[PDB]
Image (spheres, coloured by chain):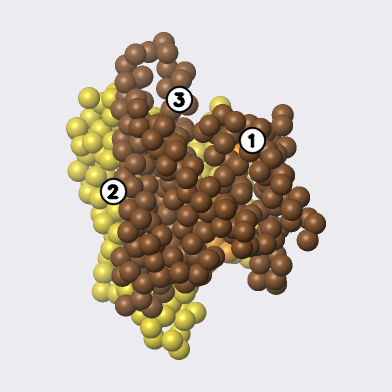
Chain colours: A brown, B yellow, C orange
Amino acid sequence: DKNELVQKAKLAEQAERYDDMAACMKSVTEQGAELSNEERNLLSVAYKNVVGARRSSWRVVSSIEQKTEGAEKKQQMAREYREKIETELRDICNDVLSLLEKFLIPNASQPESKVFYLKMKGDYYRYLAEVDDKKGIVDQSQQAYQEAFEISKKEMQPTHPIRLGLALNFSVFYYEILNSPEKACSLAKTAFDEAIAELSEESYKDSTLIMQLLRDNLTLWTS
Amino acid sequence: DKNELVQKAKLAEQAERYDDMAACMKSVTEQGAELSNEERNLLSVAYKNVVGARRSSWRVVSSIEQKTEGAEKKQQMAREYREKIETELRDICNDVLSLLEKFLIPNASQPESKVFYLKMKGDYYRYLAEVAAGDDKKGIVDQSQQAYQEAFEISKKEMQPTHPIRLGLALNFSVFYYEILNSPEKACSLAKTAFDEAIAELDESYKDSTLIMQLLRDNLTLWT
Amino acid sequence: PRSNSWPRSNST
């Protein structure tokens, strides 16, 4: 049932077993029904920990091989091990992207729902871009950001956390992927300054936290 | 070969993929070769992280089952989820205990290695005791104590109270008396004597020895 | 209480 899968998902989050948490939310998405505001957060947190454990493992293995220029034997093992983590990382994102294009983005009803699933699409394409097909994944990542940025800019407030969160992930995409450290600083600063000019009790925390991360990204980029 | 599996296990540790690290070191032991001073540390760190995630998950889910009394659905879900973690937790311990009994403990030619594997045997039986329901707990607790007791007799005989293996054995043995056997007095007696004898002998590897002695005094303060 | 035994760009 839907109640049992969500209840076990909340339980798997407490036990910190995100593979079970993602499998439950995948089954909720497989049932076609539009996820509520709580379910889309549980689905996101689940796959963010699953896909993030392979990202962190990939950054470590590749960084080790950079110092293995002297030994060609260890360089192969580090290369083979990195590729196995890459294959794991590719299968996770394609799993999320398949659910996004089949069950999620299609049935996106109300506006706030349409913007969240649209941000999630560009993220897991950005995670694939971190690892010929390069420009095909990078542009496929950019369209979801722009399409969601137009909708959030036109019908949401600059104080809504979903609009602020999308501006953050969009600005990171320009710096890390496109190597455009300056077109992103404008987006991060505008979304920040458009909010300080202006919010509900159930939204300040997520809203104010993202603005803190926005100025922390601007400070880091401007070394 | 051996050096290939050990090097890959060192990579899995840095990547924090301990399930990959455990399978690599399990194959090194399954070759019948007596582990070196570094190969047994990698095997230990591997399965301790593998077993620790189930233990940490078991405590949380069990706490929820105790707290959700009154709501049978929220409590039965926790019960069933706990039971699945228990099955994962039991298979891991049985994998290490069968690995210790078939390859590691018999081939141990040094008392340093023998106390290490015996302490390791008492630990994973103790991890099974934290989860046992009945009928089998009596034997699992006894098998844990026998491995601990044999390790304690060899270490006290041929190791010094400043040796980190003897201090760590006294630490885990005292925890066994306190939480498993519910003997909070022999636990303090075991920890205090090993802590005082280490100072009295004091009266490289000393970084590990000083840390375990701080853990002994901390367990004494918590148990008091 | 339990007994004792023995730089990057941020996103959302």
Residue lying at 43% horizontally and 86% vertically, measured from the top left: B71
Mark 3–mark 1 Cα distance, whole angstroms, equals 32 Å
**Residue type highlighted by circle 3:** Ile
- Secondary structure type for disc 2: helix
Figure disc tally: 3
In the image, farthest residue toward the right? A197
Q: The numbered mark 1 sits on a residue in which chain?
A: A
Mark 1–mark 2 Cα distance, whole angstroms, equals 55 Å
Measuring from the top left, give residue A136's x and y in whole percent.
38, 35
Q: The numbered mark 2 sits on a residue in which chain?
A: B
Mark 3–mark 2 Cα distance, whole angstroms, equals 30 Å
**Residue type highlighted by circle 1:** Lys
**Residue type highlighted by circle 2:** Val
Q: Which residue is denoted by mark 1 in the rendering? A: A183
Q: Which residue is denoted by mark 2 in the rendering? A: B96
Measuring from the top left, give residue A72's x and y in whole percent.
34, 13
Residue lying at 67% horizontally and 48% vertically, measured from the top left: A213
Q: Which residue is denoted by mark 3 in the rendering? A: A64
